[PDB]
Length: 125
Length: 115
Image (cartoon, each protein chain N blue to C red):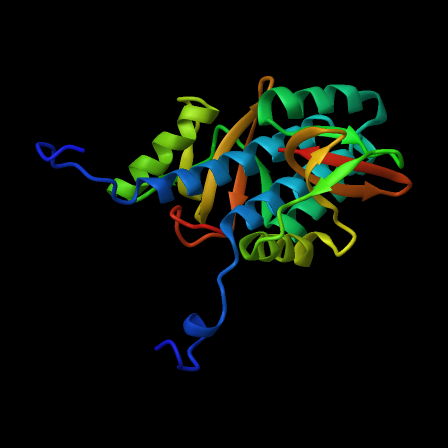
C-alpha cells in the first residue's frame, strides 16, 4: 500500500457517472428513433420531451454552436462520452443560441442533436 | 446537525443507481412502445448488443427471486417504484439467471429488462 506516489482519486468517479448517463440518453434516444413506426414518431418525440426532457433537432450545416467551458471536469466528461459515442461527437453548451447540453448523433448519413435542459454539463439528473 | 430539522439531515437522497435504472427502463420502454412491429427484432438486438440492455418477454410461468431484504435495497426499490409504478417487479434472478431484473408492461404484453 504505497507511499511514493502523489496522485489520489479526486472527482473522476462523478465524471464517469455523468458521462455514462449522457451516453445512455443519446444511445437510447437514437435507438428509439431508428426503430420507430413513422405513424407514431411525433408521439415518440413528444414522449421523450415530456418524460425524459430530451429534444431532438436536425443538425444542419448552417448550425452555429459554442463548445463547453474549457474546465478540467468538462474535459473529462467529454472524454468519457467520446470514448463510448465516437471521437467526432460534438458536445456543446449552446446551438443556434439556445443554451443546454447538446450532443450530436447520426442515423446513417442524417445528422441530429440531442438537446437537454441542463445548466451544466456536470449534472446528475 | 443530527437532531436538527434540516432537509439534508432528515431525508435520504435518491440512490443514483435507482435513478439511472429508472432512466434506462423508461427509455427502453419508450423505444419499444413506439417501435415499428417489423423492426422489433432489430430493436431488441440493438439494445442488447449496443446498449447492454436485454429485453425478454415476461411469462406467467417465470420463476423470479427478490433482492436481499436490506435497508439500502428497500430504498433503491422504493425509488424505482416511485418512478416506474408500484406494479414493478424487481428481482435478482429470473428462471435462475442472475441479474438486475426489472419488469414493465405495454398493453397486454409483459416484459423484463435485465441489466
